[PDB]
Structures are given as structure tokens and as C-alpha cells.
Image (spheres, coloured by chain):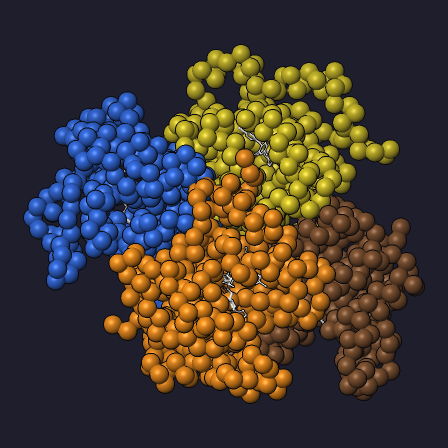
Chain colours: A orange, B blue, C brown, D yellow
Amino acid sequence: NEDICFIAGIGDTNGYGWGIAKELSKRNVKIIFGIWPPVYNIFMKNYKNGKFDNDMIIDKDKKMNILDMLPFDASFDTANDIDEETKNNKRYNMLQNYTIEDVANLIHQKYGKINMLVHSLANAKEVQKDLLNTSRKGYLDALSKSSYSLISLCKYFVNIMKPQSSIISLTYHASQKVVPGYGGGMSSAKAALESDTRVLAYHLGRNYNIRINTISAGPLASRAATAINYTFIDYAIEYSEKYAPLRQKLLSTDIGSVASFLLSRESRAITGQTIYVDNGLNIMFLPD
Amino acid sequence: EDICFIAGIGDTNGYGWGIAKELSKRNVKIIFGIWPPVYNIFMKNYKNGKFDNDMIIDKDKKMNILDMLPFDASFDTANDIDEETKNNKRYNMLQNYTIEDVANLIHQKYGKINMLVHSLANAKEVQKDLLNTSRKGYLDALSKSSYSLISLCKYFVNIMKPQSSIISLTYHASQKVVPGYGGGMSSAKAALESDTRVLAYHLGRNYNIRINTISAGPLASRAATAINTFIDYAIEYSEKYAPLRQKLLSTDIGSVASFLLSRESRAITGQTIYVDNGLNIMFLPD
Amino acid sequence: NEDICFIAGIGDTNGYGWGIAKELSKRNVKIIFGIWPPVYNIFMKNYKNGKFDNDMIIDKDKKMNILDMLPFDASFDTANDIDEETKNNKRYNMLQNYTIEDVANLIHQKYGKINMLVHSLANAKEVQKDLLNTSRKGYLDALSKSSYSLISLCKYFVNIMKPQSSIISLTYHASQKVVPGYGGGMSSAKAALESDTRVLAYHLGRNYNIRINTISAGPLASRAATAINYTFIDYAIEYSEKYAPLRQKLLSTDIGSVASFLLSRESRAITGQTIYVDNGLNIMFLPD
Amino acid sequence: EDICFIAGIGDTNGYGWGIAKELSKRNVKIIFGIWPPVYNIFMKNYKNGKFDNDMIIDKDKKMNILDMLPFDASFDTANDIDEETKNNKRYNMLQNYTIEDVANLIHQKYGKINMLVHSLANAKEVQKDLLNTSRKGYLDALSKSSYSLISLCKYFVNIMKPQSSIISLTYHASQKVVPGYGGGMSSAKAALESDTRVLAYHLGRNYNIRINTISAGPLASRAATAINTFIDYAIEYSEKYAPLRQKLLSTDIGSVASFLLSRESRAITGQTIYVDNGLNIMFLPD
Ligand SMILES: NC(=O)c1ccc[n+]([C@@H]2O[C@H](COP(=O)([O-])OP(=O)(O)OC[C@H]3O[C@@H](n4cnc5c(N)ncnc54)[C@H](O)[C@@H]3O)[C@@H](O)[C@H]2O)c1
Ligand SMILES: NC(=O)c1ccc[n+]([C@@H]2O[C@H](COP(=O)([O-])OP(=O)(O)OC[C@H]3O[C@@H](n4cnc5c(N)ncnc54)[C@H](O)[C@@H]3O)[C@@H](O)[C@H]2O)c1
Ligand SMILES: NC(=O)c1ccc[n+]([C@@H]2O[C@H](COP(=O)([O-])OP(=O)(O)OC[C@H]3O[C@@H](n4cnc5c(N)ncnc54)[C@H](O)[C@@H]3O)[C@@H](O)[C@H]2O)c1
Ligand SMILES: NC(=O)c1ccc[n+]([C@@H]2O[C@H](COP(=O)([O-])OP(=O)(O)OC[C@H]3O[C@@H](n4cnc5c(N)ncnc54)[C@H](O)[C@@H]3O)[C@@H](O)[C@H]2O)c1
Ligand SMILES: Oc1cc(Cl)ccc1Oc1ccc(Cl)cc1Cl
Ligand SMILES: Oc1cc(Cl)ccc1Oc1ccc(Cl)cc1Cl
Ligand SMILES: Oc1cc(Cl)ccc1Oc1ccc(Cl)cc1Cl
Ligand SMILES: Oc1cc(Cl)ccc1Oc1ccc(Cl)cc1Cl
């Protein structure tokens, strides 16, 4: 009764956010999407035109139920943070209550307290550049949008969450081992995120009895994954399917069912952890 | 039908039982492997109803135990048992309790299984610090606590379905110093965690079978009381300093095991997963 | 002949920068100090008034030789990055060539190419706040000054360094395990720094044959260490001296002699590494 | 005067020799512990001047070797040698080669030492994958490659000065899967790295003695050629993909060992230090 999850970072059905929504929907969790304003209207129109109907089919006995879909920008902590330019920009002008604080307030006002929170977003202006060639501003952009946004989400959402709630984010192994092409300070951002997951786990655990973990996912041909540049993601997938201990296609719903477990009471003694869902690729040193 | 063999249950106070309870919730059939020295007292307590309250899952269900078999992880095959054991009071009345014999017996009675739990450890010199542990004591720890996992996998893969899943239990003393966790137990756990990776590679590639290990926080089990109030200290420190200040239950480990043993976790393998209320993340007590 | 080291982050004789200078000076490496403008004039006056004379004594057979002392602010990559306000500020107005690019240029013009580089600096406006309570701006400040500054230093100094040169920075274990009181995103910054050390090691190793490592140091009662708030550092030191495998006072020159090794040819097969110099405290789980 | 015992030199092509060379540079007196099966061929090659070119440090200096003694890390004390070894062709002509006997002999001839190097490993089933390794094969790997370090420490601390330093060599297969590194060698290295921490605690607190381990990249030593062209592949892959694309030399490991064994590193203990041209940091070949 009333397992409600906010998923921050869905723009289509091709990423981990959607796989997570599907698996949770399967367990009858109510789902609220937080959608970035640059893609929000296109997502809504597609949704309304039934473009996602096939993708919403669970077992053909069940179909996903989505409780709400809200414009959301993890760049802005409160309304006072929004620069006049953004506020007035073509894609933002007609939207409201999309900062982290406002969206938590809106969710609370409409549905009461929630018990599950998903951070499924990242961004970096200079992702295409190697770390050495990343500018101060590009690096800080990657940290701001990909890492600090988690801390802020936690800060504002803990107020609208029940004790024993659970929070997850997504990370990538480039934080711990070198992945050429994962540029722009994304590796730095993921390293910060994994460390912040531990520190937040301490504070949230002690003060709120709330858990936080992160899933280190293997490669998935999402929309963001193309932004990296056959392309970077095509090589990653090919390499993973050839060399992982489990040689099988990694699905967004593989991450989804792990997410679902971490967000449930079944994982109540797990917190502060980086959990690898990557067909075991992370354990390998030397290829065959 | 799901069937899980759980090697290392002696009573209802350890992690093996909590894992059994949680799997039972999900309608998994459970087979216990019981160390022969305690096999007859276990059967007696069970028959006398000592475990009845511990078997209740809820209003609806009671634990279904498919079978309970003697199992000694010291011995790979029938040929490995020495005379002194053959002659032992608690062994002479039992049979087919080597790792291979148990695999063959389960397969013959019940067919193929799809879940395997290693929940056992031993070290005859656990009360000595590592520096004062003898070669025989150290190798005993590795033999009983680490190699037993490899042997379990070796003999059991033949009786397991593709997409089966295996777990063991470990402890953070492998990675950081726990004074008191002596006799090469820290060594054995480090080997277990590394072996979990290497086995994940061979089992995943050859059989599409997953293997992970759960690094559990402290629980006042029978084996824990043999370390030297060590466990009293560990539990008190964990409950005081862990990010989550709730009592760690065997079923907290059990529900994670159940997930790792299910298809829900089909993309996780070779991993050490911490189920310890977050204690492992702390650097210094606040 | 001509082992020259630039040490970025010395403001007095109480920190790791000074211990590193001493140990290198011991091996006859020439030392150039990069001194932050807020403390630069006070450092120079103290130096000129002989206040550091005792602290410069090596074995009483030898005394430290300092080749140069340059104003340096790791906040600014190039002259074009300096805001008009800073440029005109009381402490900056009378200084020149203190951005990362300008200082590399100046060093090159005066002394030619160098072969050793030390990043011994960190800053975070909100260090006193817990991570959960750190603002976006405070967090980005910590990353900018403590982590990105390393990348930028590398980017500009690789041009004035010889092949087979070596770079080190300093980090702290709070990046990997939770240290309450290490706030403001300093833990996040150190996690980024350790990850960036690997990524830089790849690029610098492959393109320049230059090594980079970081030293994870135990507690030292430096000036910065008081900024954290008996205080945070007093407890850290007390705890380290009581519980480390080696129960002995950790000296800045203990870090210095490790730094010196990492910067020398003796460590030519080590790169991308986080090296712990902390009397072994990091290996402990449970106290006695 | 500094004196270092180096256990595990068989010829001039391994890490033991490179460590000996580098310590010699710093005027450390060197004592070799040589596995009895190869002790007589080593002495013969040495006398015949086979190693003369390898002993040159430079224009100035030649390696000073204080002594060369038979040493078998399989045996803790005289009582541990079985008859079959006593009767063996290559052992019967040698004596005082157990770990305790060597410590006693060195102490009696030369007094206290202050540097100790464990540079040895063995595993009779190295060519089998972990899953197919027998209990006896696995325990042999742990016995010879891991427990030998604990025993070395146990017997040698008595003959060492306070502020002494100990190192061993390990390999990244303990932490990440290297197909080919079989027979429980990966297991033994994981135990070695964990044991390095636990020993650092006991040795640091009780004796103020430091212990670290160097995780080395691949070198075409004698033992390396026994793994199954494995080493040819490892070296080629390392030289192609490591951040530093220079040939890894035994003396690259030797200069790190020398530093860790000196007072320069007085604040480092319980650590695994990677000396591998940075290869360990890479996630996937570019
Ligand atoms: N795709 C992979 O292969 C892969 C591998 C490891 C980790 N991950 C992680 O998974 C997460 C999801 O990425 P994905 O691969 O599903 O791509 P995706 O495009 O499906 O997810 C990213 C989403 O975040 C949203 N977003 C971007 N900036 C935002 C902002 N400022 N505020 C609010 N929303 C914003 C975008 O609209 C986008 O829909 C990422 O954090 C990524 O780091 C992905
Ligand atoms: N209890 C804790 O605090 C704790 C913390 C971390 C990990 N663990 C791990 O969990 C696992 C279960 O232990 P536990 O804590 O439940 O104690 P337990 O006594 O409940 O379980 C250990 C069982 O192993 C069995 N056993 C011992 N030697 C055997 C052999 N040669 N062959 C077959 N069985 C043998 C014993 O009969 C015993 O029942 C162990 O591997 C332990 O290392 C326990
Ligand atoms: N002190 C400790 O206990 C300790 C423990 C672990 C790591 N460290 C690390 O060692 C390094 C040195 O710190 P410390 O403890 O010696 O304190 P410190 O005060 O001696 O060193 C910090 C110096 O950096 C300089 N600095 C600050 N911001 C700067 C900027 N924008 N540009 C140029 N210089 C700037 C300051 O002038 C200061 O002198 C730090 O990076 C710290 O993270 C210190
Ligand atoms: N060569 C590599 O690529 C490499 C990479 C990482 C680590 N290492 C480690 O470096 C160490 C040295 O090995 P190496 O590569 O120089 O090969 P090596 O053959 O030069 O050295 C191994 C030595 O150990 C000795 N030995 C074997 N069993 C013994 C016993 N029971 N008692 C005493 N001595 C025994 C052998 O005589 C041999 O001389 C090993 O521990 C190895 O694990 C080597
Ligand atoms: O983290 C990721 C890892 C992989 Cl392998 C693929 C995609 C990922 O996700 C991103 C990568 C870069 C940027 Cl700018 C934004 C996002 Cl969402
Ligand atoms: O690994 C453990 C860790 C803890 Cl904190 C408590 C009990 C544990 O389990 C054991 C410890 C020592 C031995 Cl000899 C046997 C077992 Cl089953
Ligand atoms: O990193 C550190 C770790 C410790 Cl234990 C003590 C001091 C440290 O150094 C700093 C800590 C915070 C800030 Cl704002 C600046 C600096 Cl130089
Ligand atoms: O550990 C090693 C790692 C590598 Cl890459 C190469 C050689 C090594 O050394 C050994 C490997 C196996 C055995 Cl049986 C004995 C030794 Cl000395």
C-alpha cells in the first residue's frame, strides 16, 4: 500500500530510468517521472500519442502504470537559483515547480510522503574531451549536474520521505579504473558520487533511518550514451558481451530488478554501497 | 520448482537458518547439509520440536524442509576420510557425507537443483593471532573455509541447472584488520572473496552459473561465541557506530541471499555484497 | 644536476608542503615555492626576517636551499580567468604572473624545464558543514580548488617538464571511508582527485612518459587542518597515535621522504597510484 | 650495517635478484635463501662466473653477497621434514634449511638483521584452473606461497632489530581475474595481501616492525615460464596497454623494495604497492 517512487532522469524508453520504472511497476510501486525541460514536451507528446505503449507492456498480462510526470531540472536547488535567462527560455517559460525543492514540495502536496527515490541522470558539457583537456567550467558542470544533484535531491527529499526509505543512483566503473573516452570529468563526477554515497549513507542512516546505495551499471545503448561519440557505446557493449563472465545482452530491466531490490525492505541492511550490475565485467583484469 | 542446498546449518542461531527462512518465503525447497559431529543432536532437537517457533514464516506459512543430510566439507570423496574419523563416535553411524557423496545423493533423490549456499567456516586455531598460527592450523582454516567452496562448486555444478546461482558468506576482516579474528580466518576469507571472482569467470563462461559472496556483519551464532565476548564487542560496536542502528538479523542476510539466488540478480556475479548496516563504510568511530 | 621541483601550496612551515621541501632539499633538488596571494607577503616578510631559519635546518650540517618563491593561485588557469575584483584586490593588486599558465611560463623563462611537480593544496568554503548541508556553490568551490586545480596544473606544466618527470598530490582517506567532520565536499574532492590521478596517469604516461601519483597522508596539525574546527585535527592525531599499527608521531617529513621517492627515478614503474603514508591506520577496521 | 635476507633466488632472472642488486647499491649486505632442489646448480653457476655480468652495479661497485644458504619454505622446523625429502638426492647433502634453522644460522653467523624479503611462490597445480584444482594442490599453493610469509615473520622477528622492515611480492590476480593464473595461486596471493595487513598490525604494535607487499607486473622469470607463453602474453599486453610503455625490469621492482626496506618509508605499513607501469589502473584496452 503506497510504495511511491520518484525517478529523476527519464527522457524516453531507451535508458536505465525506464528499465527501473518497469521493474518497480511490476511490483506495484507507483511511479512519478521527473523529466528534464529540454525533452519534457516531446516526451509528453510521444506518451500521449501512444508511442510508448509497446514499451509499457510488462508481461502482456500487466502494463506499466505511471502516477505522474513532472518537469524537473536537477541543476536548480530552489526557485531562487534559476537565472532569468533559463526562466524565460523557450523550453522553460511555460513550466513551473521544476527545481529540486519545488518538485519535492509539489509531490508532497499531491501524494504525501514517498518511500523510494531514484537519481538516474548525468550531464557534462565536455564529455567528448579527455580529462586533461577539460576546462574548469566543463569539469564543474559535470560535478554540478552529475554528483551535486544527488546531494541536493537527498537534502530536499528526506523531508518528504518516510523513515526506512531508500535512495539509489547510477554510476559507472570509469570512477575506479581508466576508461578512455569517458571524458569531460564524468569519471571524476562518478568517483565523487560513489564517495558521496557513503557519506550520505552515514548522515541519512543516523538522522533519518534512510538508506542510500548506487548501482554501477554496465553499458546500455541509451540516448545519453551516444553523446559520448561504431561509437564509444558500441565498442563498450561489444567488449562487455565478449569478455564478461556472463556473455548475454545487458538489459535496462536487469538494472531495474536490482534497483527494485535495493529500494525495497528486502535490502534493509545494505547502505552506502556501490553495487555492480554489469554481468561481472568489473572483476576481469586480462581478456582472453 | 526451486531447490536450494544449504551447507552449514547446526541450529537456528546462524546465517544458514536465516537464509533458509527467507528462501522458504519464496517457496524454495530447502535441503540442509549438517556437520556430522552435530547431525544427531540437530535431528533430536528438530524431532523434539525445539525449532518449531523458529520455522514459522508467518500466519500463512511454515518452513518446508525437504531433507537434512550429514555433510562434512573437510572431505571431497569417500577416499578422503581418515581412519580416526571412520572410527569416530559421531561419524561411524553416518554415511555418504563427503562433498561428492552429498551431491550424488541429492541428485539421486531429488534431481537437479538451482541454488547453492556455502554457510560454513572452521579454523582449529581461531583463538591465536595470525603470527602465532601454525602451518597445520592455517591450512585447516583455508581447507575448511575456502577450499570447501571450490570443491562444493566442482561437485555440484554437475547437478545444477544452467542459470543456477551460488553464494557464500564472508567477513570484512579479509580486507581490514580485526584483532581477534585469528587462526587464518582472515586469510581464508580473503581467499574466499578472490576465489568468488575466479569461480564467477569459469562458472559464468562454462555453465552460465553465477556466484557471489555476502560480507555479513556480526551475529551471535554458535561459531561466533568461539572467537576470543569478541562477538559481544563486535555487535555492540556495530549497533553503536553503523550508519543504521538497528539490530542485524540473520533474516537481513537471508533476504539478500534470496535475491542473489533468484533470477532478479541475473546481471550480478563475482561480487562481495556487504550486508552489515553499512558499518564497512566508516573510517573512525564518531 | 638540475632536479627542479615546483611545490604549489606552501604558506608556512607547519604543513606537508614544507616537509616535502625539506626532504627534497636534502637530496639536492632545487625548490620553487608557489605561494597563495592571501598569505604571500606575510610568508615573504617572515622569511626575510629569519623566522624560518630554524625550520630550514636539515641535519645542522645542511640547511634548505630555496631557489625561488612565486605568488600562485590555483583558482585561475590563465590571466583571462582572473575577475576584475580579484585583479584589483588589496592582496592581489601588486602581484603578477600568478595564474597556473603564467607561473609555468615564468618558471620556464627563468629556469628552463623542470622534472618534479607537487600539488600540496586544497580549499573548500563550507568545510565546516556536513556534506548533506553543503550548498551547490560550496561543493563546486571544493572541487574547483582542490581537484580541478591538479588537472590544470598538469595541463600547463607538462609543457615545461622533461619526459620521465613525476607529479604528486596529497589526499585523505575520507574519500574512501566516512570521516565525520571532513565536510564541505572535501571528501568528494579527494575522491575526484584520486580517480583523476588514474586518468591523468594514463594520458600523461602515454603522451609524455610522465608519472602521477597521490599520497594519502595521515593527520598533521597544519594551519589548514585547524580550519576544520580539542578540535577535529586534535582528535584525528590522538586517534591515529593510539590506534595505528605504528604508534609514533606522524611528521611532515615522513610524507616528505615518500614524496621524494615518488618524484625520483627510483619509482619509475609506479603511476596512477594512491600511496598511504599514515602509519598504517587505513588498514584497521575495529579498534582495540 | 644493514643486512637483508632474501628468500627465493634461483638464478638472476627473477625479482629476488633485482631486489638484491638495488639493495647492494645502497651498501646493504645480502644473504640469499635458495630452494634446495636448485641450491647446488646455483652455487655451480655462481662459481663458474655465470652471474658475473649480472652482479655489476656500475663502474664503482659489484654486488657484495654475504652468504648463500639452502632454504625451504615448506618446512618450519627440523621436525617438519618427511623421510622422502630427507632421502632426496638434492636434499641429503644439505642441512639446516628449514625456516627456523635458517633464522638461527644467520643469527649465529652474522647477528641481528634489519631487512627481510619474501620472494617466492609455488603451487603444484598452477596449470589447472581454480575449479579443477585439488584440495592438496590448493593447500600446497597456500602453504608455500602465503603461510611461508607468516612463518618467515614468526622465526625472523627474534633475529631482527626494532624498526626493521619486511616485504613480499604479490600479483593483481588476487584482486581481478587472470585466466591462466591457476592452482590456487590467485587465492594464495589474496591471502598474502590480507595477511600483510594483519601482520602489519601485530608486528607494528609489538615490535615496531613494518611489512608491505609489492604487486609486480610481469617479468620473464623461471617460475613465470611454468604458467600456461602465459608470460609472453602478459608482457606483450602490459607493454602495449600500460600507461608507461617501457620494459618492466626486475630492478624497477628492486628500487621500490629498497625504499620500502629503508627508513625513508617509516610511515608506510600493511600496504600493497603496485609496481607495474600503472597497468592495474586500466579498465579496458584502448
Ligand atoms: N547508459 C549506460 O551505458 C550507463 C552505464 C553506467 C551508468 N549509467 C548511468 O545511468 C544514468 C542514466 O543514464 P542513461 O544511460 O539511462 O541515459 P538516459 O539519457 O536514459 O538518462 C539520462 C537522463 O537524465 C536527464 N537529465 C540530464 N540532465 C538533467 C538535469 N539537469 N536535470 C534533470 N534531468 C536531467 C536526461 O533528460 C536524460 O533523460 C546516468 O547517470 C549514467 O551515468 C549509464
Ligand atoms: N556470525 C557472524 O558474525 C558472521 C559475520 C560474517 C560472516 N559470517 C559467516 O557466516 C557463515 C555461517 O556461520 P555462522 O555465523 O552462521 O555460525 P554457525 O555456527 O551458525 O554456522 C557455521 C556452521 O558451519 C558448520 N561447519 C563447521 N565445520 C564444518 C565442516 N568441516 N563441514 C561442514 N560444516 C562445518 C558448523 O556445523 C556450523 O553449523 C560462516 O562462514 C561465517 O564465516 C558470520
Ligand atoms: N594536514 C593534514 O592532516 C592532511 C591529511 C591528509 C591530506 N592532507 C593534504 O595535504 C595538502 C596540504 O595541506 P596541509 O595539511 O599541509 O595544510 P597547509 O595549509 O600546510 O597547505 C595548504 C596550502 O595550500 C595553499 N592554498 C590554498 N588555496 C590555494 C589556491 N587557490 N591556490 C594556491 N594555493 C592555495 C594555502 O596557502 C596553504 O598554504 C592538502 O591538499 C591536504 O588535503 C593534509
Ligand atoms: N615474474 C612475474 O611476472 C611476477 C609478477 C608478480 C609477482 N611475482 C612474484 O615475485 C616472486 C618471485 O618470483 P619470480 O617471478 O622472481 O620467479 P623466480 O623463479 O625468479 O623466483 C621464485 C623462487 O622461489 C623459489 N621457491 C619455490 N618454492 C620454494 C620453497 N618451497 N622454498 C623456498 N623457495 C622456493 C624458487 O627456487 C624460485 O627461485 C614470486 O612470489 C611471484 O609470485 C612475479
Ligand atoms: O555514465 C554513463 C556510462 C556509459 Cl558506459 C554510458 C552512458 C552513461 O551516461 C552518461 C554519460 C555521459 C553523459 Cl554526459 C551523460 C550520461 Cl547520462
Ligand atoms: O566469520 C565469522 C565472523 C564473525 Cl564476526 C563471527 C563468526 C564468524 O564465523 C566463524 C568464525 C570463526 C570460525 Cl572458526 C568459524 C566460523 Cl563459522
Ligand atoms: O585534507 C586534509 C585532511 C586532514 Cl586530516 C587535515 C587537513 C587537510 O587539509 C585540508 C582540509 C580542509 C581544507 Cl578546506 C583545506 C585543507 Cl589543505
Ligand atoms: O606470481 C607470479 C605472477 C606472474 Cl605474472 C608470473 C610469475 C609469478 O610467479 C609465480 C607464479 C606461479 C608459481 Cl607456481 C610460482 C611463482 Cl614464483
x, y percentage for residue D213? 58, 43
Residue D244 seen in the figure:
yes
* A28 or C217, nearer to the observer: A28
B76, above or below B131, in the image: above
* A184 or B141, nearer to the observer: A184
Question: Residue B37 falls in which quadrant of the image?
Answer: top left
x, y percentage for residue D244? 71, 44
At 79% from the left and 25% from the top, the residue drawn is: D53
B152, above or below D262, in the image: above
x, y percentage for residue D134? 39, 27
At 71% from the left and 67% from the top, the residue drawn is: A135
* C274 or B6, nearer to the observer: B6
At 50% from the left and 26% from the top, the residue drawn is: D127
Quarter of the figure with the C terminus of chain D: top right
Q: Is residue D94 left or right of residue D15?
A: left
User: Residue most toward the left?
Assistant: B48
Quarter of the figure with the N terminus of chain D: top right
* D272 or A164, nearer to the observer: A164
